[PDB]
RNA sequence: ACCAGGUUGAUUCUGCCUGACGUGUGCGCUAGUCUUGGGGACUUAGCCAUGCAAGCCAGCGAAGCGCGGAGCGGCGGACGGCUCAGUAGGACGGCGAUAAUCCACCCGCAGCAGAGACAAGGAUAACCGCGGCAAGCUGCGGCUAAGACAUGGACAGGCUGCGGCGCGGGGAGGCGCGGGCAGCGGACAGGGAGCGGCUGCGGCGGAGUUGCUGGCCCAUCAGCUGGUAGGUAGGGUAAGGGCCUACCUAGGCGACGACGGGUGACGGGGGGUGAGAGCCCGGAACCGGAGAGGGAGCCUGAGAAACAGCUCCCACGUCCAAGGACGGCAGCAGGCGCGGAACUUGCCCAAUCCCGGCGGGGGAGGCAGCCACAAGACGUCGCACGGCAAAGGAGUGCGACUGGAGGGCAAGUCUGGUGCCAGCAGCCGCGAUUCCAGCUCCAGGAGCGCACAUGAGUGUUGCUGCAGUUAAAACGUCCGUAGUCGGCCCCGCGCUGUGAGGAAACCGCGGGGCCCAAGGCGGCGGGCAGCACGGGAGCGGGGGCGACAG
């Protein structure tokens, strides 16, 4: 039948908060994003991850913190960049699940290769270093990417370099 | 009616309370069917009959350039207000114009009294296209 | 990535594989199958004809001759 | 034709039902085959599922048993003496189930005197049944349904079952 | 609508067949053969999705035309033939003999068996009825029927029937302590030993089962297929052996205990 | 889990209005690329030109010149597709029942009449001619087939009545089977491409009935009911039944809301929105129902009260040589009409599948086109390659608007015009910080604005959780029945835990480098005041108190 879909972004409830409208834009001008939707996607993706953790810390079933909590932390470590949890089953999950609630949207915004090109001093010009991604100059290990919100992983983070 | 076995009494009672709620009162009565102008369907389209002189509610003193319009789907004669300064000369008699509401849930907007609908397109081309000159009336 | 098949005879190839892929290699076109719109009208005329075509065409032109 | 549905009926509370859909063949009934006496004519019907139901239109004889001795004959039907549901059905001599009918006594009295030759006590046990036999009156009920089976089988009335019915006609 | 449904939608197909959503609108409607539709899969699923002999129906038509497929010792040259639980698919080309059986993922799986295990199959009886002339012939759940069996064979028993011979060679009763296979339900594809039988006069006898691992579950006895007595298994067991490992056990192997 | 503006000279409230957010429907302006999905449901279940959409075959095999393919015969056309008018329970959902029932394909079993039997009888279509007729359609003659239609021949199954012990199953029996007497009745005279017929038992696949239960509004709808409620008996049906009839009882339902009405009501899986309780929606993928212009009746068949079958009536429409003949796009495109509102008279069976015993057919279906309708990702021209049923695209490969700038509300007391005019403004408001332009600036951004509807805002519907001295609101009083609520002590039921069984889609979660993403695909879960088991408490039953209860 039909393939399912979802809404990536959301809009704020009060659209003209002058306090928010510059705290958005400094988080936007740091990473040089196209629009607020690119920022509000990661602000949503970080939020329901925080909303996921807050419903695991409430849980009565300790199997749930075992199954979904280690799944959430490995999601933070492997595809994300968290890089500190042992998964020991010595309740370092609950030490780290309460570290999920302090994560910002900017914690996810740095993970994109638009930022990661700048992390190894590769193109030095973030406001138009995206021109090199858009014209296919940045190449991960064997494949070229023209999607600057690529969200690079743990293992892939060193293996980035410019190609021609 | 607060006992543990009062659910059918509470549903019977609170529904009779809810009939006094004005938002639920219109859905209960079906007033959007009683006036087929803009309630059940948006964008009523009809034939212009005459240009109307109507004066704004005081303290504001101006003259809004309304028009009577007879609808095609109903034959109802409703008055509609023309926005977008100087547009009243761009619409003529026996035109077929489309009408929209004011965003006031069926009431008058601002200084205009009685006029609950406003024109957006004349002869299936918009007034925003004519107020700036983007399109042309056929 | 290529998913390729390794047959053992040309005859099992043209039998098992679909008819368009042997048109890719060699261009057989063994069945004409005129066109879909032509084959519909050709069959739909044959459906209303009772009996053989020769009895129907003879009775038709005999009335056309008159 | 006639239907079997309750879509025309009222509800238990007396409410009238709305009749909207067209009639189905799932619930279709038929005419009463008012089976009468005459030379045998049975009607064949390809009814539901192709099975052939035979209803008797006219019907001459019935396979009637004597339950006391376990012997049977197909004696001819003479007239319906009693019908339980309506006396209209006995005036027209309509053969249905449970209809008390007057049978042909000749074939039954031949074996009945033959067993009466050996056992003399048999006639004294029910004097009323053997009273009507010498007069030639022999009565039975149809137990089969002639509109469904196409036959008029049953048993000879004897005993208190007989005196129950001869008070009814 | 109403009548014999000739078509079958892809979403309405049984999820044990493991058909994708985006494969098409329709799924292959099985023929009305030996197994019920809830407990069967067609041949045309096995020969393209499981064994992948044919990628195309034109290839699949050729395979059934040349009659190389043979299930329960009969050729069965039908595209939509319903093969069910315990039935043995034996292909003389490739010399591959498989028995259709469930998996832990609640799906049908073709389990490779030996050439000697392919000579028989197991059938759960449905009813037991004297035929005309006094022939006491029983009826299996897959629509097979056999006569002159052991009189001790009553309902819910599984019988070991030969394939190449139409007789029943082995009998397995439905008591406590028997190795059971769970055909339908939440515990589909689980192998366990029957602990208790609760009768429930009127309807739905309930069987209590603990597996080899020790996990206890309850099912209807109609969803209970005996595969062995206490000493032995009468069939080979598939991959995973019907354990149905828990989600935390799936979690603990990835990250340690 | 949010408020903000607005009653005043100022205040505190009540109170509504409006802003602020999601959603879907339409409009408007604008527009670079790609993937994916959607799209005449709402008004008109309105009207339809033209083409296409359900055909196929292996028995028999004519013409035509062994090939052949007509007709007979057979199978399907009752499925899919479309639509949502009717439907307030004939539905649907959940749980059942059918010991009250029928059956095609297919599967597994048993079987199929010795009859002259090394054998089967009369036909008819095709065809050969001769025709009628504007057309649609049809006649006469001559022959000739069968897995068509018969004949022949009864061991069984079957039917009915009566009799009647047991053996099996089932919760429960003359349900199955064996044993009886009668009356009926009743399964192979086929073939040198695989077999094909028929009878029965068991499935499968269906189907009909059916029980319990749940689900909108109106009391300015309070009493309703006559085949109505029941009994007996028969009829009828595949089948229980007031289903029907005959006779007889006087019942049946109702404030625990009957009955009647309304609905711009198909139901559900579900969807939207909210922290939640809720509120709202469900035309729309899947399931069930219903319909084919309005109807009714039916034939054939296993299955239709069929409609791309028939018969008739009605309302529209067409052709005619005037005698007659036809049409039903709520199938696919397309046209008109309707409206706010919805695409090409494209290509093809390649994929998904279905019919047919295979070569065939399939507007089911896919592919493409149209459309900013939606989701997602990304900017500011021609070869070869590549894929494709075919083409095109993907993939290598070379040569910037939209809205605003007084407050709410982010951003101008800049410039020119306008002078209570024109105009603007959801609310407050302005008449030049608000009009109309220019500039600049702000907001979102290939999108944005508007209208309508709905949710939240709203504890302004209040179960959670409102308010009733004076803001809207305690009925003049008392009695009073249903209703609802209710003292103390001392097996059944409520409640509750687990479990069964419960479709996928969906949703929640979890993976998973489709370049990312939305995804695909694979795991795991939830759903039900139905069912089973458990439960220390609670309630009944019965005694004892005698309540700052009476
Ligand atoms: Mg003739
Ligand atoms: Mg003749
Ligand atoms: Mg309706
Ligand atoms: Mg629906
Ligand atoms: Mg449907
Ligand atoms: Mg007051």
Image (cartoon, grey):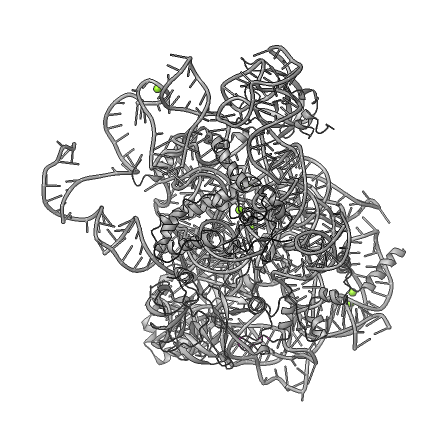
Q: Is residue F300 left or right of residue F160?
A: right
Q: Name the residue located 60 percent from the left edge and 78 percent from the top edge.
A: E93
Q: Is residue C42 left or right of residue F526?
A: right
- In this rendering, the count of numbered labels is 0
Q: Name the residue located 60 percent from the left edge and 28 percent from the top edge.
A: B100
Name the foreground residue: C51 vs F451: F451
Question: Where is residue B54 drawn, in percent x and y?
Answer: 60, 16
Question: Where is residue E239 drawn, in percent x and y?
Answer: 46, 70
Let me know if residue E233 appears in the view: yes
Question: Where is residue F452 drawn, in percent x and y?
Answer: 55, 31
Residue F48 vertical placement versus F535 (above, below): above
Image quarter (top left, top right, bottom left or bottom right) of the C terminus of chain D: bottom left
Report the magenta residues as a range: E68-75
Question: Where is residue F150 drawn, in percent x and y?
Answer: 65, 73
Let me know if residue A17 appears in the view: no
Decide whether the magenta segment is chiefly helix, strand or loop: loop
Residue found at the far right of this picture: C65
Name the foreground residue: E244 vs B97: E244
Name the quadrant containing residue B103: top right
Q: Name the residue located 43 percent from the left edge and 72 percent from the top edge.
A: E125
Ligand 1 quadrant in view: bottom right
Residue F63 vertical placement versus F33 (above, below): below
């Amino acid at each position: 039948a039909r393939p399912k879909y979802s809404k990536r972004s959301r809009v704020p409830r009060k659209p003209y908060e002058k306090d928010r409208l510059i705290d958005e834009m400094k988080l936007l001008g740091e990473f040089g994003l196209k629009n607020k939707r690119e920022l509000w996607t990661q602000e949503k993706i970080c939020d329901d991850i925080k909303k996921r953790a807050r419903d695991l810390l409430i849980s009565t079933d300790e199997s749930e913190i075992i199954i979904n909590g280690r799944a959430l932390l490995n999601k933070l470590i492997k595809l994300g960049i968290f890089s500190d949890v042992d998964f020991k089953d010595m309740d370092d999950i609950k030490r780290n699940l309460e570290k999920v609630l302090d994560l910002t949207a900017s914690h996810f915004l740095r993970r994109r290769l638009q930022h990661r090109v700048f992390e190894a001093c590769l193109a030095k010009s973030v406001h138009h270093a995206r021109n090199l991604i858009n014209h296919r100059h940045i190449t991960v290990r064997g494949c070229v990417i023209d999607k600057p919100g690529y969200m690079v992983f743990a293992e892939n983070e060193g293996h980035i370099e410019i190609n021609k | 009616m607060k006992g543990l076995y009062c659910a059918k009494k509470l549903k019977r009672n609170r529904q009779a309370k809810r009939r006094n709620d004005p938002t639920y009162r219109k859905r209960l009565l079906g007033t959007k069917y009683k006036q087929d102008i803009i309630g059940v369907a948006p964008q009523a389209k009809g034939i212009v009959l005459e240009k109307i002189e109507v004066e704004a509610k005081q303290p504001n003193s101006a003259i809004r350039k309304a028009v009577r319009v007879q609808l095609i789907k109903n034959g109802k004669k409703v008055s509609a207000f023309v926005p977008y300064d100087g547009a009243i000369n761009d619409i003529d008699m026996n035109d077929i114009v489309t009408l929209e509401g004011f965003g006031k849930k069926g009431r008058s907007k601002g200084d205009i009294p009685g006029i609950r609908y406003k024109v957006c397109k004349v002869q299936n081309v918009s007034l925003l296209a004519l107020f700036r000159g983007k399109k042309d009336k056929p | 990535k290529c998913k390729v098949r390794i047959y053992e005879s040309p005859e099992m190839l043209r039998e098992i594989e679909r008819d368009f892929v042997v048109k890719r290699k060699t261009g057989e076109e063994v069945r004409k199958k005129k066109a879909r719109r032509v084959r519909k009208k050709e069959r739909k005329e044959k459906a209303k004809i009772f009996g053989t075509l020769r009895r129907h065409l003879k009775k038709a032109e005999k009335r056309a001759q008159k | 034709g006639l239907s079997r549905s309750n879509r025309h009926k009222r509800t238990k509370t007396g409410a009238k039902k709305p009749i909207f859909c067209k009639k189905r063949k799932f619930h279709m009934a038929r005419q009463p085959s008012n089976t009468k006496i005459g030379e045998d004519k049975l009607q064949e019907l390809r009814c539901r599922g192709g099975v052939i139901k035979k209803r008797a239109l006219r019907l001459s004889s019935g396979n009637f048993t004597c339950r006391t001795h376990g012997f049977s004959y197909k004696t001819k039907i003479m007239q319906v003496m009693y019908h339980p549901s309506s006396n209209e059905l006995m005036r027209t001599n309509t053969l249905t189930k449970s209809a008390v009918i007057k049978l042909d006594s000749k074939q039954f009295k031949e074996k009945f005197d033959s067993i009466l030759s050996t056992d003399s006590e048999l006639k004294n046990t029910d004097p009323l049944f053997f009273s009507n036999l010498d007069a030639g009156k022999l009565y039975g009920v149809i137990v089969s349904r002639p509109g469904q089976c196409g036959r008029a089988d049953g048993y000879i009335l004897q005993g208190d079952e007989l005196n129950f019915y001869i008070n009814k006609f | 609508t109403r009548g014999p449904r000739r078509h079958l939608k892809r979403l309405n197909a049984p999820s044990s067949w493991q058909l994708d959503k985006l494969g098409g609108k329709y799924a292959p409607k099985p023929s009305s053969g030996p197994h019920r539709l809830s407990e069967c899969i067609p041949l045309c699923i096995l020969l393209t999705r499981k064994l992948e002999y044919a990628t195309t129906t034109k290839e699949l038509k050729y395979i059934l035309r040349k009659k190389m497929i043979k299930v329960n010792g009969v050729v069965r040259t039908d595209k939509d033939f319903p093969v069910g639980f315990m039935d043995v698919i034996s292909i003389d080309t490739t010399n591959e003999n498989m028995r259709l059986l469930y998996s832990n993922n609640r799906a049908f799986m073709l389990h490779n068996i030996s050439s000697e295990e392919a000579t028989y199959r197991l059938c759960r009886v449905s009813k037991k009825k004297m035929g005309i002339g006094g022939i006491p012939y029983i009826y299996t759940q897959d629509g097979s029927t056999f006569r002159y069996c052991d009189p001790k064979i009553n309902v819910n028993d599984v019988v070991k029937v030969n394939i190449k011979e139409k007789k029943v060679v082995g009998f397995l009763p439905f008591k406590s302590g028997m190795k059971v296979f769970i055909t339908k339900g939440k515990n589909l594809g689980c192998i366990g030993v029957i602990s208790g039988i609760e009768k429930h006069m009127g309807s739905h006898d309930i069987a209590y089962v603990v597996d080899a691992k020790g996990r206890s579950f309850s099912t209807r006895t109609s969803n209970a297929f005996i595969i062995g007595d206490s000493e032995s298994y009468w069939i080979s067991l598939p991959e995973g052996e019907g354990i149905k490992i828990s989600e935390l056990e799936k979690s603990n192997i990835k990250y340690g205990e």
